[PDB]
Image (cartoon, rainbow over all chains, first blue to last red; front, side, top):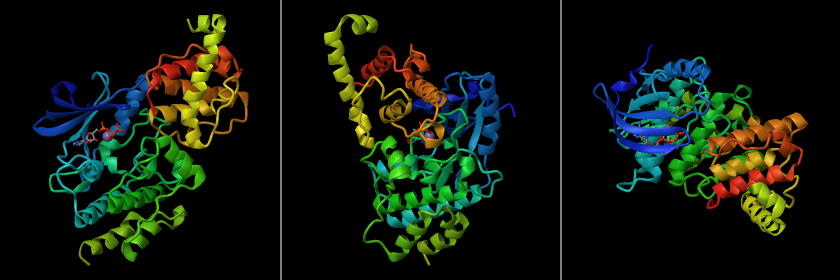
Length: 268
Length: 124
Ligand SMILES: Nc1ncnc2c1ncn2[C@@H]1O[C@H](COP(=O)(O)OP(=O)(O)OP(=O)(O)O)[C@@H](O)[C@H]1O
Ligand SMILES: [Mn+2]
């Protein structure tokens, strides 16, 4: 549990820089990878220790719809707390749905994505305790070479990583916009996020795209802002979306309950 | 510098104060919130927190700050949290103490607002 040696990483090309730090495409020990480099103000020995304790939980190799963190570089001795994960050719679900200049995925593929994500989340929901600060959204699911959707463990926020700032409130349950995690049923909150993903798969639109993140969180939390259920969809898809986005967290289904429903939707 | 502007350029100062009212309402109105008085409306830290999120593209979970502060202390904490968000956005640590904002020191408040304006000029 010394982690990955940062010097062994082959940094090939920079993909992004943002509030979190940066992302590079690279190679390590014959793996095509991305390298997430976390920039953290007031880095301390406490935060470093925390990083080294939080990372192991993300190394999940036991489910096809979960994309593990391969490993992390501890800082020190690395320049920055860094983590690595397999490179996914299609990038995020968000990329594929919203930024897909080559092709548009069909509804059968959309149903398979929903099934893949549901299976992955049901698995993650078996963990005790749950992985903290794991938020489900289309940016935090990747699409592999064979169009398999996989929950991105490299998108789980660390305890020191932008605390008190949400960059994807549109997928967050209303209770989760306002209450501390400890004061919510986290599994029900995650089902709300899945309901928004369903809406996103049905509309092929970014939820609340015409609103800033601050507007979204403030209006959903305090003004009752909701996605409008799309017109001209089967009563079955309609009923699924509705129950997953129940205003009452206690009435939302578990992931393991919706899995069989989704399975029948591929091919009854 | 800004002090010279505050203390020795009243004509400019009002043009600047004018710049700032437009600059902050450009954003807070989106929340159905209006700023008419620069002297006090940022004292409790709430609008500064909401502004930083409106300006830097994130929501602040309501459990992360005091949306309706009930004490001098909670206001201080809000301003401090806002000052931390400012530094995360790349601003240097603000010159005023968080207490100076809460105590309605106009120079202090306007300095903070001015440094925001000069940074976030082009944000829509
Ligand atoms: N495993 C991966 N394989 C290929 N591309 C990825 C992978 N992970 C992320 N990406 C791509 O890199 C881009 C930038 O991701 P990055 O993590 O920098 O930003 P983000 O996910 O929006 O924000 P956050 O810093 O909060 O994680 C993503 O939009 C996606 O296209
Ligand atoms: Mn990411």
